[PDB]
Image (tube, rainbow over all chains, first blue to last red; front, side, top):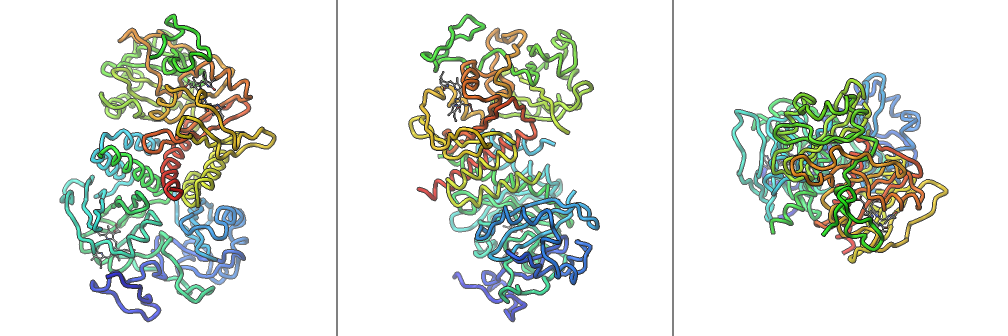
Length: 315
Length: 313
Ligand SMILES: *C/C=C1\C(=C\c2[nH]c(/C=C3[NH+]=C(/C=C4\NC(=O)C(C=C)=C4C)C(C)=C\3CCC(=O)O)c(CCC(=O)O)c2C)NC(=O)[C@H]1C
Ligand SMILES: *C/C=C1\C(=C\c2[nH]c(/C=C3[NH+]=C(/C=C4\NC(=O)C(C=C)=C4C)C(C)=C\3CCC(=O)O)c(CCC(=O)O)c2C)NC(=O)[C@H]1C
């Protein structure tokens, strides 16, 4: 039965169990993962509204100084580029990405999308022809199995993960791991089927719009936004589009029970429907640089294209 | 069928017989790079371009004897493994060579039958492709996608005119988008016949997705020997970027007023949906790392055209 969301935990909304998984409002945790920083600021005036508590550690600035300034004074060169690439009324999937030279944190990756009248700003630290060779490999795959096989090994060879899996959905939302490149000693997941209440209904929806989510350390503690609610509206901040969005404690409990430390999955969208995920497991905590994650963001599109062209020939 | 080429006593290509030219076998390359062909198993350089001495910085006839084991020691193992016998000619492998004379060279390699083809170009030593990608995806229709695709590629490439050339069902075409430098004629809106791209070109351009012409006034640099030592036949160059352009098509681009032309094939459902056309008024060699982004934007747009045209239909 599809039911609507609870309030979050910070708006008096109940604690989650296995009975009511589909009612968690995962899109509004009011908190980011600690490996980066996140501001939200005004769409038009550039007024810095909220920030993650740890934004000082990362930006080498105090909140009182930060929040008492505009994005014009803070990001003088970037601000017009933000305005130009993210005009008003544009979709929240659209991101503008840039590099900074921040004196305290070194080179900083700035990712920015708009959510109504709210520019969400992310900050991460950031540090030869392997994707091109990967591109032509996938295309010259003879069939959907050799496509799936090369994608998973390519993805592993680029990223360095313990278990990379291409996971495919079925018509009734049941899934099954169709290919994997794994670490030597790890027990296979190849050909396991998994029930429909594993990736729940509110999750699969969000995963069709935004095509890359991750979890760095399944033992880390969510860094909360400050203030937790959006001053514009006095309502939760839509952090569904943010990659720094903290992962749910239901999900973190699960991954710890498997001996997993880090997780990454690229979505594969065919016909505007979630065809499958390129999931990645790691036994230790593992942060992937944003510039390297851009390579995987590309592979998701590339694979989504070939997935279709392969299935056209299977008929 | 095709005629014999000019170098094997074939007829000259008038506008009458404009669909029987063997475009894939010109027996020559463009002067801004260097082509070597090599045997699959042994690795002996069977044929080279006459300008090879320039870019490879070696003597002319000394390279004919040597093997790719001796020449490219580190990459030679990778070429065999990455281009296995039986693979399609569309599968390319690429790497960067650090040569002693020419400096950073760009090696691109693909296999055809028993023979490998090795293309050497000069090459250089960031978030615009990511921003473009999302700019294509948030585009709310086909026309709004078409403007963003052309305007993207121009700002990346610095070309004087970037067009998007959509194909009607009977090989007729139309320009549905066109970013361009100020003070040029507008080809936005105009349609053109199906004689323009012949039957062989259209078929070849579905399999192979990027060609160019860096200089429309330069001369082709022939292969030596012209024919393939194995087969004593024409060397299939129809998957090489350094391949020379049909002399009709250069003679055309001069009458237009173009020094350098490039294109990217947008393929939807096995068929050729359209091309991304780039014109420059002057000669312009686009370097391999920048060209890679354009091939990338081809697949992206090929994907996005399918999503958008579903919303129309
Ligand atoms: C209470 C309901 C359930 C639940 C909650 C939940 N899951 C996700 C996202 C998931 N779940 C995945 C499940 C798998 N684990 C595996 O080992 C395999 C197969 C190899 C599968 C299919 C996956 C892959 C995801 C996506 C993210 C990831 O790759 O780890 C969420 C959303 C998390 C969020 O913060 O948005 C939630 C709330 N998980 C259950 O397993 C089930 C008991
Ligand atoms: C002899 C018969 C004809 C002919 C031959 C021919 N054309 C190509 C490649 C073409 N033709 C194109 C048509 C256009 N040229 C333009 O300037 C525009 C305007 C936007 C169009 C539509 C195009 C786009 C190509 C691809 C490359 C490019 O110019 O961007 C070939 C292939 C040559 C080869 O070596 O592969 C041949 C043989 N063209 C005629 O117009 C007609 C006289």
